[PDB]
Amino acid sequence: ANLWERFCNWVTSTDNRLYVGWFGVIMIPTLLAATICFVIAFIAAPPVDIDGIREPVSGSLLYGNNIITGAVVPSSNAIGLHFYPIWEAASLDEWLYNGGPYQLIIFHFLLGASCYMGRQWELSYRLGMRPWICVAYSAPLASAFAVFLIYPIGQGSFSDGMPLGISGTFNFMIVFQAEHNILMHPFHQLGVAGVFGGALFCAMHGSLVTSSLIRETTETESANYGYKFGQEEETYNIVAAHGYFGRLIFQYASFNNSRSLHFFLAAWPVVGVWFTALGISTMAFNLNGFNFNHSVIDAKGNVINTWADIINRANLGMEVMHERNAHNFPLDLA
Amino acid sequence: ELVNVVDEKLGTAYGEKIDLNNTNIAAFIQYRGLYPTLAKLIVKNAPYESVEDVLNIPGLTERQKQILRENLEHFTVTEVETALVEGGDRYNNGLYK
Amino acid sequence: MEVNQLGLIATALFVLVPSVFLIILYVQTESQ
Amino acid sequence: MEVNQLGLIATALFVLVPSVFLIILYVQTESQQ
Amino acid sequence: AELTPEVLTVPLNSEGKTITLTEKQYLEGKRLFQYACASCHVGGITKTNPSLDLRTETLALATPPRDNIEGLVDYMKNPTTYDGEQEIAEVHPSLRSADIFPKMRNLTEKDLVAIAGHILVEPKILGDKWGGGKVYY
Amino acid sequence: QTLTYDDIVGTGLANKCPTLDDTARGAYPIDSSQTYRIARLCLQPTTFLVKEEPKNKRQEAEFVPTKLVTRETTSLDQIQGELKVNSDGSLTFVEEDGIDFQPVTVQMAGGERIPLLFTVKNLVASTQPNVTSITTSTDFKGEFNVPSYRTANFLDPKGRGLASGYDSAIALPQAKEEELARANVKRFSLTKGQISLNVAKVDGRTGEIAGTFESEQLSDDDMGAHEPHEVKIQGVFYASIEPA
Amino acid sequence: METITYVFIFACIIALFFFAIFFREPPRIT
Amino acid sequence: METLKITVYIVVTFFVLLFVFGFLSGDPARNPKRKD
Amino acid sequence: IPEKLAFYDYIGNNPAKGGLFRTGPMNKGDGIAQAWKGHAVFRNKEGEELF
Ligand code: CLA
Ligand code: CLA
Ligand code: CLA
Ligand code: CLA
Ligand SMILES: CC(C)=CCC/C(C)=C\CC/C(C)=C/CC/C(C)=C/CC/C(C)=C/CC/C(C)=C\CC/C(C)=C/CC/C(C)=C\CC/C(C)=C/CC1=CC(=O)C(C)=C(C)C1=O
Ligand SMILES: CCCCCCCCCCCCCCCCCC(=O)OC[C@H](CO[C@@H]1O[C@H](CO)[C@H](O)[C@H](O)[C@H]1O)OC(=O)CCCCCCCCCCCCCCCCC
Ligand SMILES: CCCCCCCCCCCCCCCC(=O)OC[C@H](CO[C@@H]1O[C@H](CS(=O)(=O)O)[C@@H](O)[C@H](O)[C@H]1O)OC(=O)CCCCCCCCCCCCCCC
Ligand code: HEC
Ligand SMILES: CC1=C(/C=C/C(C)=C/C=C/C(C)=C/C=C/C=C(C)/C=C/C=C(C)/C=C/C2=C(C)CCCC2(C)C)C(C)(C)CCC1
Ligand code: OEX
Ligand SMILES: [Cl-]
Ligand SMILES: [Cl-]
């Protein structure tokens, strides 16, 4: 054992309170940089000219935001997709005005989070586990890539990336509806199905295992004290929960293989969230939601509005008001 | 003391007629014959003291002065408003459809 | 920013009162 | 009256902080018994 | 309501002589107006020059006037500016410029009359929606 | 030399006016029977200075330097106009057209951003009388117009504008309007600035001149909402002079 | 004052992270 | 700023090298069952 | 006379003019100094200068 090997063993040690890992050797610095830049910027960054029209948007607390309205504001549209590291600016004052912190944070963050995924694989290998938790995390990771990288690439600017704020996130959702009619896109409908049903099945599983917990405590103590960490036996009667739940609907609508039951819980929301991340990724290239505007017309040819035309009226309200000083020509093509 | 100069102008002849000193060039589509040739000439030769100085534009043709007389009743001149003529707003005022 | 004066006292007690409850309950659990 | 607005948060914490300290110490004394 | 001959009656020339189209032609002109004109003219606006719509009242103050089928077939053969003072076949598809605007090659005089019929009928049906743009969608 | 966009793209040189050797100290003969024109005039600012503003004390306002934050986007170029010979021998430049304005934001100590419309719109600059030739001691002085930094369609964060926009503070339905007038009522400023151009290099061969300039003008006033700052711009210019 | 409040509460949460991880109840194999 | 550029260049490079070399240092054997 | 020297000659900057519960900056009290108004000379109807 020499210097390199002692280090290699520390890095991949399964005795560290927090696993490090080769993926962690990248994740730790990139996440730290992003987290420190994000916190300073959120509190103190001065206004950022997000839309490139010399009209700065104040995102930080010290400049009169609160927790809900504050943000790290995306980098200037004048920058488009150009790389804007600190060293490319003439002064930090220039880097701040033009929104450099958003580039630094998102790049370090996306790098950091891709290696988090990798680190989940890595530790599972050292622990003797099956490897695929990192596959589940890939649904939220891709989702984040979609709003922070892909959608900017398709539209040619990080100025149309998702802002790092609570209200900025809403701005981003609203403008998206106007430009892509995302509600009418099947992949986002799959993501709603992803998350409603993931919440639905999460209550169902909690409610059902909780229902069939085996008495092991008295009325005064928490029932939680009837499980002991590491115990070999199960704390609940799955036969009984299948018996409740098979009758609630019918016998075959109900799982009786615990393995089949948990793979279903993993698979449902992960798939759904893959699809909505893909929906954001593809609407990045302007393949938008179904367009049924004026799809119904009468014998003479008058337009017979459906609910889709009513959506489109709201969409148009979003369209004409958003970024109200930034368009000189009549189509908003990116 | 603080007034919107554009609202003020709406209460003038500008609000009823084509102000040859102010109105964006697309308002000349309203009347047969004017657009785009004469409107460009009208706009280029800039401001006028009187509506009828438009007939003295150098190089007009006889067909053109006749069209212009046919429409003197649709024109007016008021003072030039910096806010309507700056930024090239007489050629493109941000309005499309 | 012209914010609410009572907002500070409402926020502070909102944190302080329920937190102290939990702290009282936890420390006397430990000492028995 | 034109009284100072932090008078109130000052008074409330002056009361609550040391009161809670003592309550914490007393309660966990009694559950030692 | 339905599609009637009173609706399908449109000016044939500026002297007043009308012609009365049929269901089959109006649909042909909508289908050909799509193929040929909707890219810039969808809904009766003009995307590459919003100041100029296909509203029947705009085609009236055109020089030469255009609110009749002959006037329109002529525009589609040899188009001009609104005042008539210039020919714009170089930047506006027409039979004249069918070499640079291929979609115009395979059209016949009956096709052009279908397309004008459509244009002159469509505002009878939709009114202000035709040539209004997004306010009216 | 023949330089191409690809040689230049991305370097910062697109924002720089041409220069001449230190041997371009000739003299261009000006010929009264002739008409002349500036085929290109190019101004490249190098420093933006912004007048301080004392307290009540009427002490002293110095021009403090500023930090440019809007990058290499500041130069006026491609400007053309008639160089008239006048009867008192002087030369007068009357601008016609060009990229004669660039909006600019500089920062002051403390964090205040000062935007301004760096411009020479409708420039009319004249030399001294009886100028037979442009030498490396020839000066122009002139005045230009400075239109409002934003034009009439510009809408403020609450949707208010001059030619468009809400005419009131809609989020405060029943506030007293009196206290909000300066902000509810956009006004479009139009002002004048002064500029000295000092020819320091001449190429009589080609009729190329180059020197430095100094201009004074007002900053953005935000369509009437606050007072402008006095701003002083220094840089270099280059002009080619063709017979017209 | 409201800036200070937002940041104080943020900072309290970060300290809570530190203790919840490093001074957790250790899980025991019983 | 040039000083910053170079410091980040050197930093990133060094970490990037840990990651590669680390995985090359017989990472498939670093597991609790088959040391191979 | 520099205004900075005249401002020292003013009891409002005397640290012994305060109070225990009068909180905050001195500016919260007499206000933010903007200008020296001038040095003031009193005379009676006789032309005698008074102090
Ligand atoms: C795991 C470590 C890690 C990683 C992967 C990154 C990654 C990045 N940083 Mg961050 N950074 C880190 C740690 C890290 N950082 C730390 C610890 C700090 C604090 C000091 C920072 C501070 C920081 C700042 C202040 C900035 C970045 C920026 C960036 C981005 C571009 C960096 C670049 O051009 O390098 C290029 C990398 C290479 C050329 C190395 C490639 C690897 C090959 C294999 C070798 C190449 C040899 C190389 C050229 C020789 C260099 C020496 C030579 C000059 C003598 C990228 C997201 C910039 C940014 O976000 O802009 C938007 C930026 O402004 N970083
Ligand atoms: C009145 C109740 C109601 C019902 C029945 C639905 C139903 C639906 N909504 Mg809506 N939704 C509701 C209220 C409701 N919604 C409300 C109050 C809001 C907020 C205003 C929304 C907002 C919303 C959005 C934004 C979207 C939907 C979508 C959907 C679809 C997916 C549902 C899903 O995955 O849920 C999770 C539940 C499950 C996965 C369980 C299975 C659900 C199915 C539908 C029931 C089983 C049917 C069964 C085969 C029939 C019995 C046959 C028998 C022989 C066994 C579905 C058509 C999405 C959509 O448009 O899809 C078209 C979509 O994008 N919902
Ligand atoms: C009932 C209404 C309803 C419902 C249920 C949904 C549901 C959803 N929408 Mg839709 N939306 C709606 C209405 C609705 N929407 C309306 C009305 C509009 C129009 C105004 C839209 C417009 C819209 C847009 C434009 C987008 C959505 C998206 C989404 C998704 C959000 C969750 C997500 O991305 O998870 C995925 C998970 C993540 C993004 C999290 C990633 C986490 C990273 C990897 C780690 C984070 C670490 C963190 C920083 C630190 C944590 C550590 C710390 C705690 C210590 C989801 C499928 C988004 C989508 O599909 O994105 C892909 C999207 O971009 N919506
Ligand atoms: C050596 C300590 C020290 C000193 C000399 C100062 C001095 C100053 N501070 Mg700082 N400050 C300090 C510590 C200190 N500070 C600390 C520790 C904090 C964090 C709490 C602050 C936070 C702070 C803020 C947030 C602000 C100041 C400001 C000020 C100025 C106004 C002070 C004022 O009005 O006080 C008034 C003094 C009192 C009201 C006296 C309080 C003492 C009471 C009467 C006693 C308490 C009761 C006690 C229990 C007695 C019974 C006990 C018995 C049983 C034995 C002044 C220059 C202010 C300023 O002008 O900002 C620029 C301002 O806004 N300070
Ligand atoms: C006048 C009149 C008519 C009155 C007379 C009435 C009367 C008394 C006479 C008889 C009436 C008669 C029977 C006629 C019927 C008429 C008729 C059909 C009525 C209409 C009813 C109808 C519309 C119902 C639709 C059915 C419906 C609501 C749901 C079906 C959808 C469905 C199958 C989805 C459930 C999804 C599913 C299978 C499970 C996933 C959930 C999940 C992950 C749970 C987690 C989980 C599962 C487990 O499994 C176990 C184990 C554990 C641990 C666990 O975590
Ligand atoms: C082991 C854990 C350790 C964690 C420690 C946390 C790290 C803390 C991060 C803070 C680092 C930022 C400091 C930047 C120094 C500013 C100097 C300066 O003059 O600029 C400060 C200002 C920035 O801008 C001005 O900042 C002011 C702060 O009050 C005001 O807010 C003004 O309004 C704002 O405009 O700009 C300048 O004056 C200089 C122009 C640029 C020339 C500086 C070259 C150095 C480039 C900085 C690169 C930072 C890299 C940080 C990574 C280090 C982490 C190991
Ligand atoms: C005709 C048109 C053109 C062609 C189109 C082709 C369509 C057919 C494609 C078929 C797809 C293949 C099946 C899927 C894989 C599978 O079978 O899993 C294998 C397991 C094994 O089941 C288990 O099987 C076990 C035995 S064994 O392992 O299968 O051998 C048994 O022990 C256990 O009890 C039992 O549950 O399946 C499950 O556990 C059963 C529950 C059903 C869930 C599986 C599907 C995944 C759900 C995602 C839904 C996405 C929603 C997105 C959000 C809106
Ligand atoms: C499909 C064959 C058609 C038909 C039938 C028409 N257009 Fe166009 N159009 C375009 C532009 C820029 C103009 C304005 C031209 C100008 O005067 O500068 C027009 C104008 C017309 C008119 C005149 C309408 C009027 O109000 O007078 C008419 C009758 C007309 N068009 C018919 C642009 C385009 C295109 C962009 C490439 C396309 C394609 C077409 N037009 C297609 C057609
Ligand atoms: C060695 C090692 C390690 C460690 C490492 C680490 C731990 C790192 C760290 C890192 C770090 C620690 C980093 C940092 C970064 C940061 C940054 C980069 C920041 C930035 C900032 C800035 C840039 C800002 C600015 C501003 C704003 C925003 C506003 C206001 C003003 C100012 C100017 C301040 C490990 C374990 C892996 C293993 C291997 C080896
Ligand atoms: O930046 Mn942000 O937002 Ca997507 O389109 Mn174009 O751009 Mn702007 O407009 Mn709509
Ligand atoms: Cl917006
Ligand atoms: Cl645009």
Image: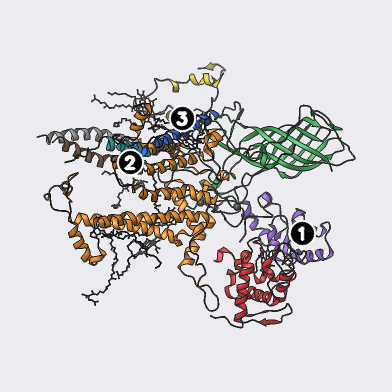
Chain colours: A orange, B purple, C brown, E red, F green, G cyan, H blue, I yellow
Residue pointed to by mark 1 = B51
* Relative depth, front residue between A30 and E61: A30
Give the spatial CA distance, label 2 vs label 3: 64 Å
The answer to whether mark 1 and mark 2 are in CB contact below 8 A is no
User: Which amino acid type corresponds to the residue marked 1 in the rendered image?
Assistant: Val
Residues marked 1 and 3, same chain: no
The quadrant holding residue F35 is: top right
The quadrant holding residue F203 is: top right
Residue pointed to by mark 2 = A123
**Which residue does the image show at 39% across and 49% down from the upper left?**
A138
**Comparing marks 1 and 2, which lies closer to the viewer?**
2
Quadrant in which ligand 4 is drawn: top left
Q: Residue at the top extreme?
A: I48
Which x, y percent locates residue I16?
A: 39, 20
User: Which amino acid type corresponds to the residue marked 2 in the rendered image?
Assistant: Leu
The quadrant holding residue C29 is: top left
Q: How many marks?
A: 3
User: Which amino acid type corresponds to the residue marked 3 in the rendered image?
Assistant: Gly
Residue pointed to by mark 3 = I31
Host chain of mark 3: I
**F183 relative to E49, above or below:** above
**Comparing marks 2 and 3, which lies closer to the viewer?**
2
* Relative depth, front residue between B13 and E95: E95
